[PDB]
Amino acid sequence: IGIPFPDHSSDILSGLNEQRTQGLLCDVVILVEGREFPTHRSVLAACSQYFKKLFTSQQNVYEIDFVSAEALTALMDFAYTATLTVSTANVGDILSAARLLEIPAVSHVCADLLD
Amino acid sequence: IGIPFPDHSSDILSGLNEQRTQGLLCDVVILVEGREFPTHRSVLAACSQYFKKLFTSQQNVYEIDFVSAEALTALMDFAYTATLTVSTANVGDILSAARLLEIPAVSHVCADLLD
Ligand SMILES: [Pr+3]
Ligand SMILES: [Pr+3]
Ligand SMILES: [Pr+3]
Ligand SMILES: [Pr+3]
Ligand SMILES: [Pr+3]
Ligand SMILES: [Pr+3]
Image (cartoon, rainbow over the protein chains, first blue to last red):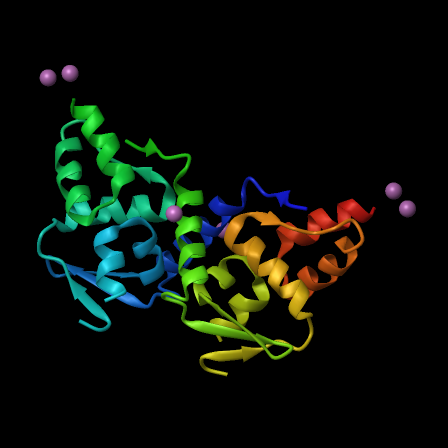
């Protein structure tokens, strides 16, 4: 009968972030403005519908031309840590990018912060 | 400045569990007592030191002969949901398996439940 581990999902995420930090067990590179982001297909697909569609339908490197390197870094950081670092002036920029990547947790929140 | 998402890691884990359930974006198969478990290398490595060592050092299928299919199913379920389903009689069995896979969250708890 289910022993609950309330810290487990965050411990998992931390471990995946360690992998990302260390360039370990990353199976895809996102390329944005000439900048490369080694990540996990699976983690991206679990929080972005753009990426789920992309990976469940090039081969190791995928270019994104419709978000800034700066927004993608903030959103990839969010994906892997559960914290979105944003300044008051940039909320609308992150909203625009999260809608295009279809990361609804971030889109809903940022839209609420703008009215 | 970090907007915190307290539900995000569990939403990520849920998404990875969906992938596992649906056989999507799984990059390894664990083989135990003739039974195959499509999973993610990255998720296994984030919670088991046995698996982190295994994957950061065959190629798509990895046999485990030192835990039961029944214990591995319970521990893989835990890995992907943050709940360990166990009966009162099986705590010691799961403890034995978690120590061999080096899943310290489960080992510490099960040892405490046995004294
Ligand atoms: Pr960790
Ligand atoms: Pr307003
Ligand atoms: Pr206004
Ligand atoms: Pr989900
Ligand atoms: Pr006692
Ligand atoms: Pr006793």
